[PDB]
Image: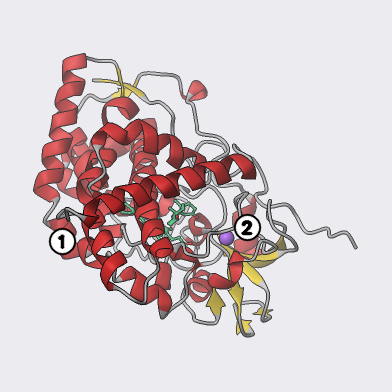
């Protein structure tokens, strides 16, 4: 009848806790029907790692199909069809070659000197201010912003402008479809004007390459190119901003974790990997994939036409994959998490986010051995109504 399929998300999120329903689903109903907050009909929620790798990793699932306004989705506005996430291979592959060179592990690693220099600079400004201080204001926000503005070639003077835009674009329930469609439109025209400036004066930056491509690639559309600029500018700071605060929260609320990194700072890369695994940065669900053919998952054959949604954080707690999966452990031998997704849409910024997180924690644990949270855990201002989780403020002392 009117379905008794449960609403997803199941609940408003609490700090970085996973809803307890996911462990129940993994063990007893790993693929299950749900109703998403927008779109029509139902979708399969996938909570286990092997199923997640098939949904994310197989041509028989299409994200392009999900651009239909009737397809279930986690966000109010229908997906933009020229957005990178809504492309299927091989069209997706051609689109990613627009920018991909700049994001290889090799080119990102070459940014470490520049990136460390910027971190130290912001922590200089924090030490000037004096303890206590808001870590979000002095580190979590300015640091990513500066990295992505250098790489893209966005002016740092526009931070306030494009952070308003990005916050709205990451709305889950916080903003309505209309408000988000207006911001979408404004961000588009803004990005298009940044790229259009390179047309009489090319720059050695990503926006530079974007502008060369609008002239010399008769297989890429200006809509796709400009949307790539917009996507990179959003994901390129909003993820790491949140993840810096999230990692710091995990470290300070069981100080032993932080103390182990203070004692041994070369453990930081591994810790970053383990906290990526453990942190439900993506608040709930994922970009929907629609089966274009019947596909076998662990417990169910998804029919052609049926949508699916992966919960990344749930797959990252799969007990068949990780030992003591509900525990945070910086000395795991194996960590095949999907905090950065999997398959064709594997995060393009994965190496850059790793670099940023490593340089931010490494600097903290070496310079601020005495760092602690200097506001009550009860009052922490968790962002509400967004597709990702993180803190609006994090006052710390040292
Ligand atoms: C640690 C921080 C980050 C996390 C946890 C993260 C997580 C993810 C995840 C899970 C996906 C897959 C979404 C899906 O397939 O449904 C993804 C895709 C993506 N991420 Fe990231 N990301 C991070 C940092 C970044 C950065 C720094 C950038 C840009 C420089 C970026 C840009 C993207 C883009 C463009 C995609 C879409 C890729 C595609 O469709 O081909 N992300 N990210
Ligand atoms: C930025 C972006 C929208 C927000 C996405 C981001 C990929 C990673 C991610 C995971 C989600 O499930 C939604 C929020 C985010 C953070 C997307 C890449 C392109 C798209 O425009
Ligand atoms: Na979607």
Q: Give the image location of residue 393, x and y in percent.
A: 40, 26
* Mark 2 Cα-neighbour bin, 10 Å: few <14, some 14–19, many ≥20: many
Left or right of 165? Residue 116 is left
Please tell me which residue is depicted at 64% across the width and 61% down the height of the picture: 25
Q: Residue at x 35, y 39 (%)?
A: 241
Mark 2 highlights which residue? 73
Closer to us: 168 or 190: 190
The colour scheme of the drawn protein is secondary structure
Residue 139 position in % (x across, y down): 27, 31
Residue 11 in sight in this render: yes
Q: Looking at the figure, which quarter contains the C terminus?
A: top left
Question: Image quarter for residue 331?
Answer: bottom left
Give the residue drawn at x 31%, y 58%: 350
* Residue ID for mark 1: 107
**45 horizontally vs 199: left or right:** right
Q: Which mark is residue 304?
A: none
User: Considering only order in the chain, which callout, 2 or 1, is on the residue closer to the N terminus?
Assistant: 2
């Amino acid at each position: 009848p009117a379905d008794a399929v449960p609403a997803y998300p199941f609940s408003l999120p609490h700090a970085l806790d996973l809803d307890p329903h996911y462990a129940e689903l993994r063990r007893d109903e790993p693929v299950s029907r749900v109703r998403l907050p927008y779109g029509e009909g139902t979708a399969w929620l996938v909570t286990r790692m092997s199923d997640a790798r098939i949904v994310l990793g197989d041509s028989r699932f299409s994200t392009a199909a999900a651009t239909d306004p009737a397809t279930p989705r986690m966000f109010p506005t229908p997906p933009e069809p020229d957005g990178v996430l809504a492309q299927d291979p091989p069209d997706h592959t051609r689109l990613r070659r627009l920018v991909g060179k700049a994001f290889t592990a090799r080119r990102v690693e070459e940014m470490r000197p520049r990136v460390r220099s910027l971190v130290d600079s912001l922590l200089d400004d924090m030490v000037a201010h004096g303890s206590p201080a808001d870590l979000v204001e002095f580190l979590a926000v300015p640091f990513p912003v500066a990295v992505i503005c250098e790489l893209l070639g966005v002016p740092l003077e526009d931070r306030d402008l494009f952070r308003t835009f990005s916050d709205a674009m990451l709305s889950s329930t916080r903003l309505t479809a209309a408000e988000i469609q207006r911001v979408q439109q404004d961000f588009m025209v803004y990005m298009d004007g940044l790229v259009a400036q390179r047309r009489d004066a090319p720059t050695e930056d990503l926006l530079g390459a974007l502008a060369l491509a609008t002239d010399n690639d008769d297989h890429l559309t200006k809509g796709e190119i400009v949307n790539m600029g917009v996507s990179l500018l959003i994901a390129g700071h909003e993820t790491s901003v949140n993840q810096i605060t999230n990692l710091v929260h995990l470290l300070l609320t069981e100080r032993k974790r932080y103390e182990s990194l203070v004692a041994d700072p070369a453990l930081v890369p591994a810790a970053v990997e383990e906290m990526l695994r453990y942190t439900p940065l993506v608040s709930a669900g994922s970009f929907v994939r629609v089966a274009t053919e019947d596909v076998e998952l662990s417990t169910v054959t998804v029919r052609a036409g049926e949508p699916c949604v992966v919960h990344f954080a749930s797959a990252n707690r799969d007990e068949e994959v990780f030992d003591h999966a509900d525990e945070l452990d910086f000395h795991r031998e194996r960590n095949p998490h999907i905090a950065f997704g999997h398959g064709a849409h594997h995060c393009i910024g994965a190496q850059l986010g790793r670099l940023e997180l490593q340089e931010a924690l490494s600097a903290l644990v070496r310079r601020f051995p005495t760092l602690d949270l200097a506001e009550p855990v009860a009052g922490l201002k968790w962002k509400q109504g967004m597709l990702i989780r993180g803190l609006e403020r994090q006052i710390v002392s040292w």
